[PDB]
Amino acid sequence: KETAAAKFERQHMDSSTSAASSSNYCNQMMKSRNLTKDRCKPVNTFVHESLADVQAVCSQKNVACKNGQTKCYQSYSTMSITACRETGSSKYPNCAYKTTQANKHIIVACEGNPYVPVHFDASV
Image (tube, rainbow, N blue to C red; front, side):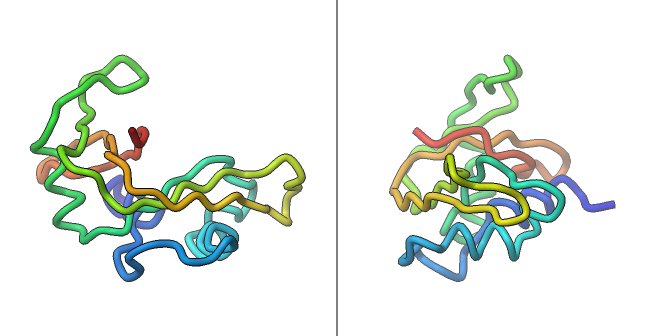
């Protein structure tokens, strides 16, 4: 099935746009990345950097994940990101999202050999 690295790339990588310009960016991107297929995925974050930049985060600041494991890494520098949150008036299959564009440090869980992002934990 899909590898954890490619799932992280489908759910969280959007290098070809430097930033979200539209309020509907999340409605479009959550639909086309297959995150509203059987359910509205309530929370997602897209990262607007190159794959090599995002993968370099796995050799940067080692920190604890929310689940208590220390396979997480915090980026030393801020990155262009867009957070997607399902709103109160959102009902499947018509999923509605608030788009929040921001320049924030990201924290990703890294795993495997090669050692790459498999999970987006948070942004700080």
